[PDB]
Image 1 (cartoon, rainbow over the protein chains, first blue to last red):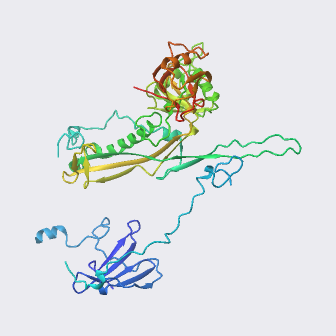
Image 2 (tube, chains in turn red, yellow, orange):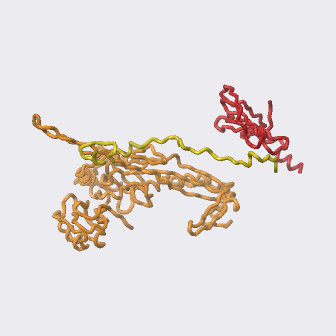
Image 3 (cartoon, one colour):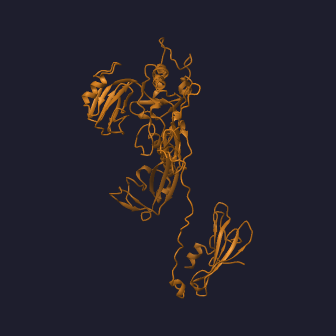
Length: 97
Length: 49
Length: 394
């Protein structure tokens, strides 16, 4: 499944371009409280519920991969564009306004 | 016993060995568990900006 | 922001004509001064904690014994010293317009110039006391031995000078010479007026100035060893250790704030609010000369040596002096400057009251003498920091 950057975030090792670890944060229907969170590590993935104002004990699952099961799609203007720039370019923003 | 510097005998208490015979550091076996808020348990959290 | 600033840079007068096609390189550029101490001395693995050097000290012993005469008991002994790295630093700062233009590659120039200055600040804190940090142990100017080289360098180094090392049981392993020394090597001649250190047609440089050996010891040159009376050194350069905690480090920003005055007289400026850009520089060094006595200072002509002598406020017992290894009488803990002067001039080697000078007060003396002066405090009975050392002044 694909997830947007408004719900999943991932750290990158700038030495190797490998994803280090990543978090999925489900805001509730209110769009302001995180009602569950999931952490992807290289060895395993684990998840907390956040009903009743504080984290429940995490459920967990291993996956045995050498690497975290998250892959970044990115827009990439250049080789220098290490994290990928928005396609709504600053000149197009300027002529829209 | 003998003086902590005795001329005839080499002892672990002698000032001569003070660089080597240190006590080893260990886990704090008495470490207190962290507190937590009680209000955030009993009060319903309301989503807010 | 100000303009023509005494600390910052703002398209200052330095950069007049920076864009002009008629500007060439500095055809008269002078090569960068390296440290020499970091080239002659043993580099040691070092870290932010500092390091401990252990050393043995015990006079372990055995005795001859007859059959059945029951054997003696003995014990060894050993000791600890430690060295902590000191830290050296600077900042330089420029307008973003200067950083954009980079006139005459000023930024690149400035990085390499401050790198030489940090190396020379270490070097000049080791060969001499100059602004030295508290955590360094010793500097070579303390060494209490001198030698004139000028009339004939061979008699100077290999005979007269080398005597002063071996008499104290110190080795001679290297010699270090300033560029200004060269005329004395060229002028070192036999009685027929032919030079010693060069082959018969006098085509080539004298062998020490090829970095060749003198009497089996290697010779090291430098552009910048000489200061005050002193043109170079000889000694056991195996007695020096030094070390460094990571690379010469540059960090850069425009976000931060600088004080342009002292901590007690602050004059803060935001880098951001004026659009200035600043560079931080740091390095972190340790040094230890294991025995300051194991060197000889080299001078052109002969010179007097000056000593500071302090008795740690001891109010009882008698100390004694020794000059070039010949002992004085014993001297009281509160003797006058005149009483110390006459007790020095009484030494049987031929010292005299026109050469010897003494100044100060009871328990706190400066002495000037034409030799290696030393003192024994073991006959004092009321203090233990009692000490003597060489001192040098402008």
